[PDB]
Image (cartoon, rainbow, N blue to C red; front, side, top):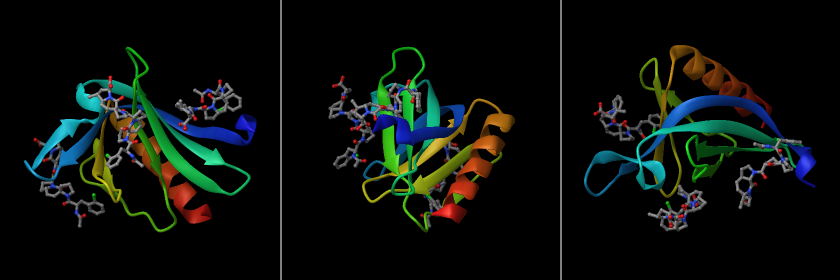
Length: 113
Ligand SMILES: CC(=O)N[C@@H](Cc1ccccc1Cl)C(=O)N1CCC[C@]12C=C[C@@H]1CC[C@@H](C(=O)N3CC[C@@H]4C=C[C@H]5[C@H](C)C[C@@H](C(=O)O)N5C(=O)[C@H]43)N1C2=O
Ligand SMILES: CC(=O)N[C@@H](Cc1ccccc1Cl)C(=O)N1CCC[C@]12C=C[C@@H]1CC[C@@H](C(=O)N3CC[C@@H]4C=C[C@H]5[C@H](C)C[C@@H](C(=O)O)N5C(=O)[C@H]43)N1C2=O
Ligand SMILES: CC(=O)N[C@@H](Cc1ccccc1Cl)C(=O)N1CCC[C@]12C=C[C@@H]1CC[C@@H](C(=O)N3CC[C@@H]4C=C[C@H]5[C@H](C)C[C@@H](C(=O)O)N5C(=O)[C@H]43)N1C2=O
């Protein structure tokens, strides 16, 4: 059930997607602002996903599988990004610590997939 899926990291970040047509970053879910972003581990099938919800109103702005082999790119010390088939995601972290802790947890997840 639900309890077999566990959060293994959370951080504060503004979630963005790249508008491939207009060549600009846009807020995930339509409104710019900070979200609480988790990496969840489904222990039964050993899969991971990233889920983020806006802090002010809990809107779900990202719910993204993390497949085996995903390339997680640290573009700057506070902006990280990865590819999904439908769009590129970016996380603008609220602090360097948020970014580094999230990235480490992501790299650990990628190495156990
Ligand atoms: C913040 C947090 O995780 N608290 C958990 C804390 C906790 C407590 C006990 C053990 C484990 C955990 Cl981790 C929580 O208190 N509980 C209460 C029981 C349930 C849960 C426990 C585990 C799962 C993990 C995953 C998350 C969940 O349910 N999530 C994430 C947001 C995501 C968003 C929307 C909905 C969508 C409508 C449908 C579906 C969709 O995304 O398809 N879905 C979701 O999947 C929604 N769980 C929980 O919330
Ligand atoms: C597999 C996959 O990645 N699929 C993507 C979506 C996708 C499918 C096919 C091709 C490309 C893409 Cl990109 C996905 O699921 N993504 C992309 C990031 C966001 C989301 C992740 C989670 C949440 C859960 C809720 C839902 C959501 O956000 N929906 C539903 C549609 C509905 C329409 C409009 C907007 C309105 C502007 C504001 C608000 C309003 O109605 O108030 N709203 C919404 O509520 C909007 N999510 C998503 O779409
Ligand atoms: C091979 C591959 O897939 N490559 C991807 C990246 C990637 C590599 C490996 C694995 C996965 C991925 Cl995903 C790629 O290159 N992609 C995917 C997204 C589009 C982009 C393509 C072109 C542009 C060029 C510029 C850069 C960009 O977007 N950058 C630069 C840093 C800079 C920092 C912050 C944000 C700021 C919050 C808003 C805005 C601002 O500064 O105004 N901004 C930015 O401008 C941000 N691009 C990209 O990243």
